[PDB]
Image (tube, helix red, strand yellow):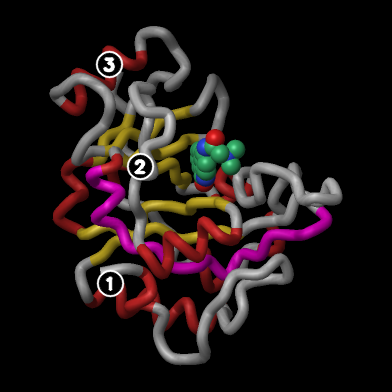
């Protein structure tokens, strides 16, 4: 069960620096409805490079054994697309010093997994956070079949980290929010977010209920 199964009608979708081909907000609305019908729920945005986007959508979300041992390892997403937007690019530059813009993805999880999503009131960089999160999830870090949401730093927007096992149960489709080839390293323009996407982007109640501290 990968995002490729949930793209709806229309042509073949592909990721490009000039936007996701054959993807529109109207198509997203159909896809979203298909995912909801099958029991999935939207949990946030994931920004990544083009090739990674393609892998995630058509091959599925899989851990790639990166930063093993790091207690905060997992699949990073954000309810606010602006936070994800910053990571939507190639990591390493081209042969000629060009870093291409990436893509914004929408991440869906089976509804029955929602009880494993937790929120902290602490910032995740605070030295106390690891221990507070371990108390929420009931086991030592790293995250497993569970997720944590909290601020990245004080005042920061809130990131959600899915444990890799839980992330393997997600399905991911493209967002209709574009990235800008001129605005690599930059901030998302709020006005490029389609209103009709916003309307289907509410998060579950763990994300707004007071964080645990
Ligand atoms: C520099 N990055 C492209 C690679 C990386 O080091 N990690 C990583 C890589 C991709 C990421 N994409 C996300 O949407 C995101 C959202 C909230 C918080 C973190 C992330 C995120 C983090």
| Residue labelled 1 has its Cβ within 8 Å of some atom of ligand 1 | no
Q: Position of residue 206 (x, y in %)?
A: 29, 42
Residue topped by disc 1: 36
The N terminus - image quarter: bottom left
Residue topped by disc 2: 207
Q: Answer whether labels 1 and 2 touch (C-beta < 8 Å).
A: no
Say if 104 sits above or below 207 in the image. Answer: below
The residue lying toward the viewer, choosing from 76 and 44, is 76
Left or right placement of residue 177 versus residue 56 in this view: right
- Residues packed near mark 1 inside 10 Å, few (<14), some (14 to 19) or many (20 plus): some
Sequence order check, earlier mark of 1 and 2: 1
Give the Cα distance between marks 1 and 2: 18 Å
Q: Position of residue 144 (x, y in %)?
A: 22, 35
Residue at point 78%, 59% (across, down): 181
| Predominant SS of the magenta segment | loop
Residue at point 43%, 66% (across, down): 57
Sequence order check, earlier mark of 3 and 2: 3
Q: Which mark is residue 128?
A: none
Say if 171 sits above or below 151 in the image. Answer: below
| Residue labelled 2 has its Cβ within 8 Å of some atom of ligand 1 | no
Q: Which residues are magenta?
A: 165-182
Q: Position of residue 103 (x, y in %)?
A: 60, 60
Give the Cα distance between marks 3 and 2: 17 Å
Asked which quadrant contains residue 163, the reply is top left
Secondary structure beneath label 2: helix
Give the Cα distance between marks 1 and 3: 32 Å
Residue topped by disc 3: 132
The C terminus - image quarter: top left
């Amino acid at each position: 069960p990968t995002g490729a199964e949930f793209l709806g009608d229309g042509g073949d979708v592909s990721f490009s620096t000039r936007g996701t081909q054959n993807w529109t907000v109207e198509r997203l609305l159909q896809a979203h409805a298909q995912l909801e019908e099958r029991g999935y729920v939207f949990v946030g945005y994931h920004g990544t490079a083009l090739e990674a986007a393609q892998s995630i959508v058509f091959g599925g979300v899989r851990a790639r054994s990166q930063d093993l041992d790091a207690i905060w390892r997992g699949f990073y997403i954000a309810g606010d697309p602006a936070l994800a937007y910053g990571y939507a690019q190639d990591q390493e530059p081209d042969a000629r010093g060009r870093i291409a813009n990436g893509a914004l993805l929408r991440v869906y999880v089976p509804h029955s997994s929602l009880p494993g999503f937790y929120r902290t009131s602490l910032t995740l960089a605070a030295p106390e956070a690891a221990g507070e999160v371990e108390r929420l999830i009931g086991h030592p870090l790293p995250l497993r079949l569970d997720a944590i949401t909290g601020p990245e730093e004080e005042g920061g927007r809130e990131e959600t980290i899915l444990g890799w096992p839980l992330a393997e149960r997600t399905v991911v489709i493209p967002s209709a929010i574009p990235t800008d080839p001129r605005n690599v390293g930059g901030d998302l323009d709020p006005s490029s977010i389609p209103d009709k996407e916003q309307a289907i982007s509410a998060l579950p109640d763990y994300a707004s209920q007071p964080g645990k501290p």
